[PDB]
Image (tube, rainbow, N blue to C red; front, side):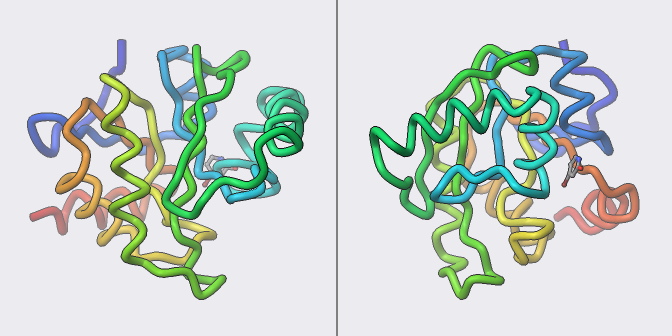
Length: 165
Ligand SMILES: O=c1cc(Br)cc[nH]1
């Protein structure tokens, strides 16, 4: 299963790892994507996950959007995990660099509660512009299922562990 994770709470675990590499090694049941409402996987975790699937995630996502329209900020959809996981849970956290309401981050993490175990990034962190310390706090206070967080940046991982209440 998952290895080298630091236990933060009863159900939240954290590791300094590349989520693509982590997904390829573990092949978890669910890998969470840091998605946008259009499922346009251009950069960040989304761009990296999509590139690992040889663009198959984008082709599948475009068909999903053509049929269903965009997701809501705070919402999600379950699609194939391709070569990375059984499923990919595309979760839309608020993008602070788009003026989106940071209060929607709790709604975004609530999507994780529909899955017993997930490999995930910190929602709204990185290119989404939110404070990753706040995202970890919302994660631990919202997610009740087993979440294994992959934090790409070593310096951010150290700051998150060292400042964890
Ligand atoms: O290129 C990337 C970006 C993020 Br964030 C995580 C993994 N790889």
